[PDB]
Image 1 (cartoon, rainbow over the protein chains, first blue to last red):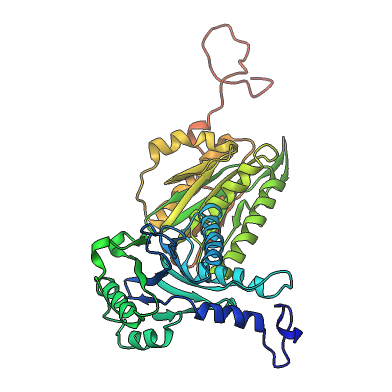
Image 2: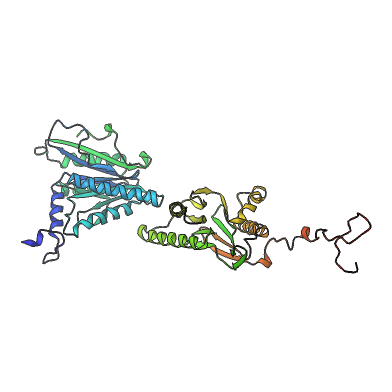
Length: 230
Length: 229
């Protein structure tokens, strides 16, 4: 009926169905994984290409928000770009008004508040993407996930996308206390390669980024010759 | 107005006079120019009282909300940046010289000077107010960096006393506050117990020989203090 056409309407059981539909759109997107390794955060996403003529690096889903913070997008890429722009605005406001890098928890809370505001008004629709915030700020390594509903949660390891449950199960086999980013990059790449179906997504690429002590606490992409071939 | 802040190894000491003067009349002789921003961060205010009070209240309100938002403490650099921005956007309408001094667990004790122009300089020590002009050569000669907490407090009080001994716009009580990893501690010493004043200085006891008695000689023999003599 008309109980699921706009976000400003609660259902008879207290649900917002448009947000659930946006989350369903997120659940049909490419798989992403992330791990907090007690010395940094490593995020790895799979990019599915519908053409073999795409230039390398096309449709980047991992974007640096600050020097030490970055966001991976799982879902509608343009919505993720808007969220990344908002996060970059939040990060530079802290560096300009308060003369300090934005803490990972603070940035995650700002992203969640921004995403939640689009689930309360009839004139807007919720974002169709989940945001993975990887930061190495003065509060240590931080890994957060922001839901299209606007709720944020901190994780040691997290998986999102179509092949989410199997990737989460593979992540359950790690220790996350002795785990280091150097081996975590390979672990996440191997998990993404193993969990991906090779007969439906012919063109696939693994895009991995990280921010730990080895990059001077700067959120950058991996060196090209570090991820496994497959 | 005489304000200053000096950094020691642990934290900072902020010192100020207590005198609000309407040109040549003392409107207030027990002012408090050390204004609390956070628990461990304070500011010394010089210039327009209303402008500095409004600036400090606005910055303190901004910082109090920021602590709740981030759930952690505030660095001295954040308060210095807040004053620098707010004083730079209003530099043509306000008359304010600010010293932002405090302690944070990350950078220890910090002192920042924000003059009337609106700049922000991180310094080991900062001076401000009309009476600061008397202290520069006092710091070049008598100040040695690396003093202890008590030594820093004593030196700050002595410097403030020397400053308002010569400055007519400064005087009254000397207020000091120490900000470090421990509990901040304040102190107010009165004028009659001040570490220095020219009234108690033995080298200014003898009066200048101006009122010569009528004499038959060019020899100078002191002032005439009696009608007969």
